[PDB]
Structure formats: C-alpha cells, structure tokens
Length: 57
Length: 37
Image (tube, rainbow over all chains, first blue to last red; front, side, top):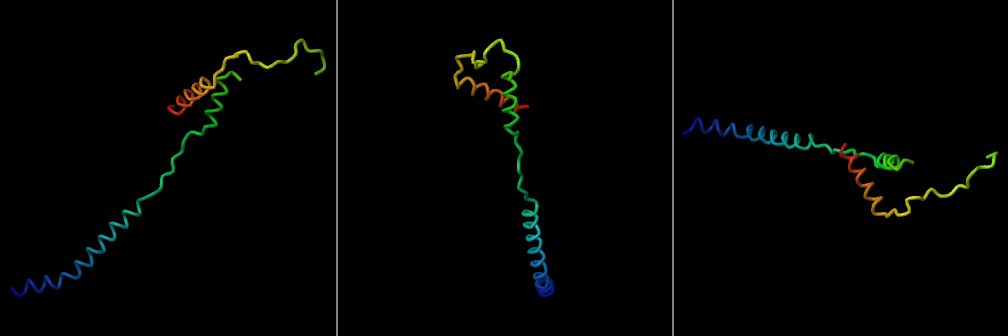
C-alpha cells in the first residue's frame, strides 16, 4: 500500500523518458535506411545499331 | 573517280513494297529480344 507504490511512482519518469528516446531511435532508423534507387535501362542506341546490322547495311 | 565507270548509280530500292508497319514491327521484335537478353 505504501512502499512499492512510491518506488513505482519514482520509476515512472525515467522509464517514460527512455521509451520516448527508444521510439525516436526507431523512427530515425526508419528514415536512415531509405535510399532512392535509380535504375539503369538498356540504351536504345544499341537497339538502333542492331536494327541497322539486321538490315545488312 | 578516274576511269569511266560501267554503271550509273541508282537508288538501291529493290524491295519496293515496304510498309511502315512491318518495319516498326521488326524493330519492336528486335528491341524486345535485346531487352530480354
């Protein structure tokens, strides 16, 4: 009725602070590991060159 | 170009019937083949 309640009350602030920091850490990780991926596609010049070769030119 | 040539140059057009659709179709097929590879 008296002791354990008081010590729980004393614990509350530190735990709240640490959990807030942990959540911030996880969202920070979410944004950190995002990168824009630029894909590379076969240049159409080679396609045009192959078309010319097929024509026997 | 010293030396009388035997023939006068003319356009090499011999495949008179060349529809634009066929040429673009062949280009598409070649393009698809290269892309797949």
